[PDB]
Amino acid sequence: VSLPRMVYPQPKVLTPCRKDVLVVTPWLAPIVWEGTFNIDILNEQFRLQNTTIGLTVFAIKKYVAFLKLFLETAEKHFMVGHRVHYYVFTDQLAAVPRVTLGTGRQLSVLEVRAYKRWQDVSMRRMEMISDFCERRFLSEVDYLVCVDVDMEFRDHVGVEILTPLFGTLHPGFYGSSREAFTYERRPQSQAYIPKDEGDFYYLGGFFGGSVQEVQRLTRACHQAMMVDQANGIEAVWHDESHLNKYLLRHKPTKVLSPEYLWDQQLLGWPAVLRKLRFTAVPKNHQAVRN
Amino acid sequence: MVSLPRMVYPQPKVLTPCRKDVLVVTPWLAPIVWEGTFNIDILNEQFRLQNTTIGLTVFAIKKYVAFLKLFLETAEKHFMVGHRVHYYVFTDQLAAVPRVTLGTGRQLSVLEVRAYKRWQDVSMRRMEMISDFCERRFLSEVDYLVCVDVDMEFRDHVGVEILTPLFGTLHPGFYGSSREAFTYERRPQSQAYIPKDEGDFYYLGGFFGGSVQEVQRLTRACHQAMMVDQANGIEAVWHDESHLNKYLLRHKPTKVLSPEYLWDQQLLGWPAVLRKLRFTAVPKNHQAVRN
Ligand SMILES: CCCCCCO[C@@H]1O[C@H](CO)[C@H](O)C[C@H]1O[C@@H]1O[C@@H](C)[C@@H](O)[C@@H](O)[C@@H]1O
Ligand SMILES: CCCCCCO[C@@H]1O[C@H](CO)[C@H](O)C[C@H]1O[C@@H]1O[C@@H](C)[C@@H](O)[C@@H](O)[C@@H]1O
Ligand SMILES: O=c1ccn([C@@H]2O[C@H](COP(=O)(O)OP(=O)(O)O)[C@@H](O)[C@H]2O)c(=O)[nH]1
Ligand SMILES: O=c1ccn([C@@H]2O[C@H](COP(=O)(O)OP(=O)(O)O)[C@@H](O)[C@H]2O)c(=O)[nH]1
Ligand SMILES: [Mn+2]
Ligand SMILES: [Mn+2]
């Protein structure tokens, strides 16, 4: 389908986008930073295919308190102008706040089991996402975006992230070397990566892609965790550790910069970030995990 | 996909770009393939596990059959070495194709085509010929089609780093220019028309490709645009190249190849920005060879 006439500044070949940071991976996937992309062209590209973006989010037990701010900020910054179908997974149906949604956007609530330990709740996300895409076949959406709930949107998060498979760089470890990365270092684990391996440390709280790729990934990670459980082992960073094992063995077709998941309290706002888009809501871990 | 094996390679650095001297990504987030931007180990893994097959089309019409020898022999050294390759030589002379020894898992087929008298028609009619070829045997034989001029020789690596849904190549004598200077078709009456305030890049008609579905889509559309022009009594300023540039403007390429992938050393030298010269023109006499 052909793009219409558009007027915009010309891509200048001998004038780099950004010079301080890496904008492309050695397997030729983009790293998304401000000033790398023209959202006008990308919006038009994705609007011509009438793209539908699913956004999954688990708000179990005390994490329902996070829903309102998460959902309202999503209205103002997440894939605006495009079709959005939210998926809210919770143990409490009544506790989901009434959030006014812009046109072409809807919400569905799906009840799940509540696990005792906070590690299991986070881990079993992979299982529940997989079981849901299996049950729906795909149908409704073209892409799925899977994020933590304890977050607020502050700036634009649009179709630039959309690609068959994507992860995001953990804000803690983008300037760290691979032996400083907190991979699972026990060879007994299905998530084991030795000190000589690894590209990036990816976040467990922001990944996604096409439905096919996301179903594939969540299933791989859950079965990987089931073998660990049977072997009596729990991965150091739980769901995150298995995603890292997976994105090492199956490279993402785009990678997102720490612009797309930050913590201003813990890490501030360094010069390499022109925009903070998706940010940690301050939480008392021990108390909110009960 | 296909699960990658354990590999040992230098770690990519987020705070340390490979190339600070060039644009390595388009405004629509397509990689621009320069030397330094990729690790061939990783890419060779990804594709080889797919059992990827590459089709290379090339036109040897009339006197341009003389170029085939050097073209094919240099391709065997540098083009897609280690992957399944099939050469498609389109000629009006089946007895003029030189006997070139191929590596394992590599094929060559000669297809007979007519020879239009004018060189412009020879060049422009490649789009129809590639498309009729694509339709004849759908995506029956290859996963990707690469479509290149013959007045050429490989001088360095040209591999699976080029493979994507749809790619184009930055013209060597324009990569530094500004869009108003690009020699697009400027007459509103032509289909290839692009006004002064549009355009991202000036692409080459002598090096493009992509997936079988995408290439056949491109060549067909280009041929149709040309038929409409010939009916209107107009021929685009730079022929198939012009129609291609219109097509890639309206359908952005998923990868862009840097001038590394088509250069003229006799005309333009070897600038510092080009670490390699992978695929270069063979100096020719334009009036005589085109006849
Ligand atoms: C020495 C560097 C410290 C950087 C902070 C690390 O954050 C934590 O990283 C581990 C992986 O090793 C895991 O992903 C949890 C993560 O902490 C969460 O996210 C950060 C950004 C903060 O918001 C924490 O409070 C969260 O619990
Ligand atoms: C101001 C730019 C000068 C660069 C040389 C122009 O080359 C010719 O450009 C036209 C369109 O503008 C078309 O692409 C043909 C092209 O000439 C061929 O390619 C170059 C690189 C040389 O190798 C020539 O000998 C070829 O005929
Ligand atoms: O009791 C819980 C514990 C976890 N989660 C979900 O699991 C994710 C991971 O937990 P958390 O955000 O605390 O991990 P962290 O950001 O600390 O790594 C949360 O975002 C929630 O979506 C939940 O809904 N209820
Ligand atoms: O008489 C001709 C004219 C052209 N060509 C083919 O069309 C391509 C483009 O023509 P040419 O190389 O002259 O264009 P240039 O590179 O000079 O712009 C050539 O590489 C050939 O493959 C051919 O085979 N015979
Ligand atoms: Mn979180
Ligand atoms: Mn040529």
Image: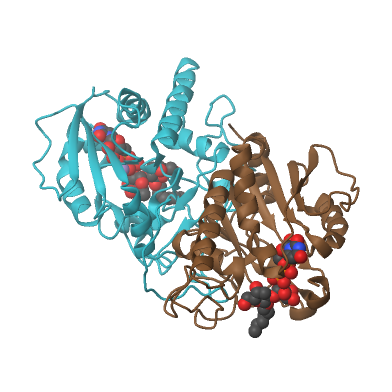
Chain colours: A brown, B cyan
Return the x and y of residue B122 as percentages of the image width and height. 30, 29
Q: Is residue B171 left or right of residue A252?
A: left
Q: Nearer the viewer, residue A54 or A116?
A: A116
Location of residue A59 by image quarter: bottom right
User: Can residue B92 be seen at all in this image of the molecule?
Assistant: yes
Return the x and y of residue A227 as percentages of the image width and height. 49, 63
Circle count: 0
Q: Nearer the viewer, residue A275 or A72?
A: A72
In the image, is residue B129 above or below residue A75? Answer: above
Which part of the image, by quadrant, shows the C terminus of chain B?
A: top left
Return the x and y of residue B51 as percentages of the image width and height. 31, 47
Q: Is residue B290 left or right of residue A131?
A: left
Residue that appears at 38% across and 35% down: B212
Image quadrant of ligand 1 equals bottom right
* Furthest residue in direction top, as rendered: B231
Residue that appears at 18% across and 41% down: B107
Q: Nearer the viewer, residue A251 or B178?
A: A251
Location of residue B36 by image quarter: bottom left
Q: Is residue B77 left or right of residue B226?
A: left
In the image, is residue A284 above or below residue A75? Answer: below
User: Can residue A6 be seen at all in this image of the molecule?
Assistant: no
Q: Is residue A123 left or right of residue A268?
A: left
Residue that appears at 63% across and 71% down: A170
Residue that appears at 39% across and 49% down: B163
Return the x and y of residue B259 as percentages of the image width and height. 41, 55
